[PDB]
Image (cartoon, rainbow, N blue to C red; front, side, top):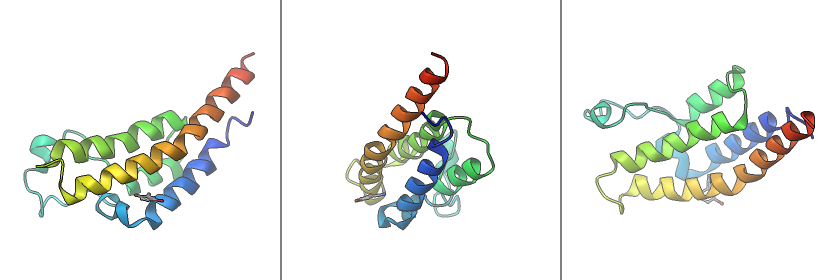
Length: 119
Ligand SMILES: N#Cc1cc(Br)ccc1O
């Protein structure tokens, strides 16, 4: 019932995501020089370095907030892709499946810890 355990669990999951080749297009903000119309479609850019920095600065209160930012990386990729068959979008789908498979226990354990704290 450790209410703080999610933070190191998220740090370790972000480390795995950074080791994965599929994360390369998402490790840093999208390059506006390569994609000059990016901000005409995407209102809120997000990337894994920003997620990691926000976590390390102590600026997430819960793993749900981290999960909302990670999911924004994937929805941005889906909204900017010109095709559902594109390379970068295809990498986003595999990364998303891996992230969701691993974040599920983090969220469940945190929510269970909070419910126990308030019993
Ligand atoms: N992150 C990540 C990831 C992990 C495995 Br296993 C396979 C594909 C991926 O995109």
